[PDB]
Amino acid sequence: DALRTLIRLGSLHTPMVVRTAATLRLVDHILAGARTVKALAARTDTRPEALLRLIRHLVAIGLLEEDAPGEFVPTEVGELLADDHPAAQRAWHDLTQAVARADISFTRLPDAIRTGRPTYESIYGKPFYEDLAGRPDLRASFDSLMTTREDTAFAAPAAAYDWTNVRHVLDVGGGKGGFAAAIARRAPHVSATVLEMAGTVDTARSYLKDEGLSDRVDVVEGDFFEPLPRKADAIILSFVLLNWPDHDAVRILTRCAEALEPGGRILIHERADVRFGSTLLDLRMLVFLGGALRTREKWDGLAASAGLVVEEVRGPLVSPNVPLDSCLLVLAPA
Amino acid sequence: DALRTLIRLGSLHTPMVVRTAATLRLVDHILAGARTVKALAARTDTRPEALLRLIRHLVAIGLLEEDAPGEFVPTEVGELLADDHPAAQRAWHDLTQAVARADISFTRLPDAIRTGRPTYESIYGKPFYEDLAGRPDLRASFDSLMTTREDTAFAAPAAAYDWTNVRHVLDVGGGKGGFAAAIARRAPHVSATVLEMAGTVDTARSYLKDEGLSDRVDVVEGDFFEPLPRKADAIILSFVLLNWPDHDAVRILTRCAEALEPGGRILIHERADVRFGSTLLDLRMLVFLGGALRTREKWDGLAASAGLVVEEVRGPLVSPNVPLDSCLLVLAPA
Ligand SMILES: CC[C@@]1(O)C[C@H](O)c2c(cc3c(c2O)C(=O)c2c(OC)cccc2C3=O)[C@H]1C(=O)OC
Ligand SMILES: CC[C@@]1(O)C[C@H](O)c2c(cc3c(c2O)C(=O)c2c(OC)cccc2C3=O)[C@H]1C(=O)OC
Ligand SMILES: Nc1ncnc2c1ncn2[C@@H]1O[C@H](CSCC[C@H](N)C(=O)O)[C@@H](O)[C@H]1O
Ligand SMILES: Nc1ncnc2c1ncn2[C@@H]1O[C@H](CSCC[C@H](N)C(=O)O)[C@@H](O)[C@H]1O
């Protein structure tokens, strides 16, 4: 009992079997009509004997079941590996896309606990975002994964703040601009600017065009460790600061403080440290990037170092469906 | 629900957190009196902030619990990570010992499914047993791990066969000689020979000496792909053949057939393919070694190729305590 529990918790084969199934698009091939192990093997370009041994573990953990002899089909849980499922778990487990690939850094977790430093570079040759800057496929899949974290498409954070006195929003590291878009739909008088890295700026521009928002949201390529491209009344850091150790996060916050208009505020949208998934995201930040999730008291110190104070934390954001784990910290000049 | 289930099954951070805790000997340090995170950090030579983030996940998965503020203790499941626990799970999860280290091969499982070939060499530079031959620390921990698979110390397989008409036993790849020892205690008239690799032969010799069996069990250093050192009435292959692809297993079986006395038998002691843990061991063999677990029908073909027939399979072996997953196949000249 206790022995079986410990063995399952410590098992490396099971998560790699799940990720291999996702990378091979196994459930998609089954749902597209691959009824036999020979057809599945052919569509995935794998050895049939080896694929069957993978399938045997997929059956044992309840992702596949045998309907007829030799005919394997997804269970209710396996169906979440279909590529069009809205939770996007296939892509989140795909070893050729940015996050599951980055998760290999966990194989060197002892080094990260001994040093406090990320292990991603020791495995892939460059730190996380520099590796993405050299790999257009990983840059693109990362940006797409970041748009599948929550089901409101930033509607819930955009609704948690009053935009009446805001004329311009600067979305610092704003990904493909989904947050800037949600504010624009919410608040017709606001204009916005997204500051992002090379590669990402082009998909942000295409996304904002296709929303019909090109006239209201601009995109600037740049580095948020440098002086920001313009001033704004609200400056958004959405899942940015957790990517960075304290001294780097203070540098970013300081650049934002310097770009605030009088009366402006900085909005940090992030999962706060205090259930489910908190330790996964925190340890991801450690081994990918050297970042961390932060408590309120930790945020107080970071803000003070940047000439700011935490005015308000708008607690875990609500959706009609699956709850957002994230919060909105509102920061003002000290 | 289904989403949380899939996310837990696909999680790489949880098994690496367990293995990191085992490698750091975290539970041993707690039980030896490390009551604070600062004391634990000092004994494990880790950063206190990073160690706490590891501990937070260890609490979330139920291996540790907080007794007093800042004082972490093993749960009933965490206690199995104590190094002296008889299930030996600490060593089985220790990333500096041979098996948990080998499990990193699972990070390249897609390659193994595409090619049918093991991934261990692509990661560590040499195939499994050649890597052990160059690493005395891994050779030794592997040999020790192989003595902790079952709780009877080979008493159950030794009791599953009638030794009356056996005068000499050859234990081919017999590890530290634990199986030869169990037969010797069971059957006072039998002498035995263990055939093993360099390094392992010395710990076999020390173990057999310390059992008081040096006069009854010899150890020979050699290669079981070469002609065997002598003939015997029973030739044991205990958790050997699953290490090898079919053609290599046939070579071994053939060497054994050539060394059988008239009326002799070959005993294969292995987990047969047909619950819990079957797919783990099978996929381990794939990615470590290119081996596999085999069904009865597969064994029939291998035996026939070696000039043998399966006479009898003595089904899953029984213990008074935790059941042995293994079986004993009895093979005779065709
Ligand atoms: C179901 C929750 C969630 O889908 C969304 C959660 O927000 C979240 C996840 C993963 C990542 C991030 C997340 O925010 C990142 O912010 C992130 C990052 O920061 C910009 C830089 C690199 C990688 C990641 C990352 O892999 C997922 C999770 O399971 O974690 C518990
Ligand atoms: C609780 C079961 C068990 O403790 C014992 C089970 O017999 C078993 C295990 C691990 C290994 C082997 C086992 O036989 C090997 O034979 C082996 C091997 O073969 C000689 C060569 C390299 C690695 C291994 C190996 O890691 C464990 C397990 O959990 O697997 C489901
Ligand atoms: N120096 C830098 N300058 C500008 N953006 C950077 C940067 N370093 C990292 N980033 C960006 O920071 C982002 C963090 S991922 C978060 C994206 C988006 N805000 C969201 O909530 O979904 C990435 O898109 C990355 O491109
Ligand atoms: N070419 C070879 N010649 C002899 N032994 C070999 C060998 N290749 C691998 N081995 C041995 O095969 C063993 C398989 S592990 C099984 C050990 C033991 N029979 C038990 O049941 O516990 C290892 O000890 C390894 O040293």
Image: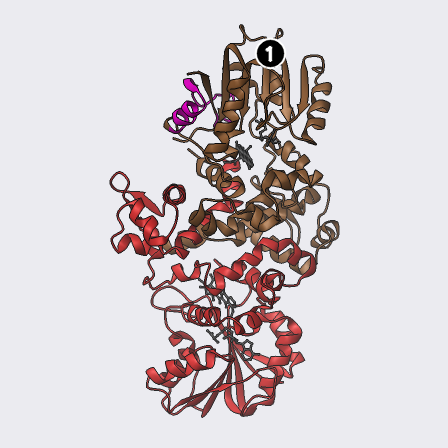
Chain colours: A brown, B red
As rendered, which of B295 and A266 lies closer to the eye?
A266
Whether A321 is among the magenta residues is yes
Q: Is residue B131 visible?
A: yes
| Residue A81 vertical placement versus A52 (above, below) | above
Residue position marked by numbered label 1 in the rendering: A168
As rendered, which of B307 and A275 lies closer to the eye?
A275
- The kind of residue tagged 1 is His
Q: Is mark 1 within 8 Å of ligand 3?
A: no
x%, y% of residue B185? Answer: 35, 84
Residue B155 image-quadrant placement: bottom left
x%, y% of residue A55? Answer: 61, 53
In the rendered structure, the residue with mark 1 lies on which chain? A
As rendered, which of A197 and B92 lies closer to the eye?
A197
Q: Is residue A117 left or right of residue B319?
A: right
- How many numbered tags mark residues here? 1
Instruction: Label 1: state its secondary structure.
Output: strand
x%, y% of residue B206? Answer: 38, 82
Q: Residues within 10 Å of mark 1 (few under 14, many from 20)?
A: many
As rendered, which of A1 and B27 lies closer to the eye?
B27
Residue A154 image-quadrant placement: top right
Q: Residue at x 65, y 32 (%)?
A: A144
| Residue B228 vertical placement versus A251 (above, below) | below
Residue A300 image-quadrant placement: top left
Q: Is residue B41 left or right of residue A96?
A: left
x%, y% of residue A54? Answer: 61, 55
Q: Is residue B314 visible?
A: no
Quarter placement of the C terminus of chain B: bottom right
Magenta region, residue range: A298-326
Whether A305 is among the magenta residues is yes
| Residue B287 vertical placement versus B330 (above, below) | above
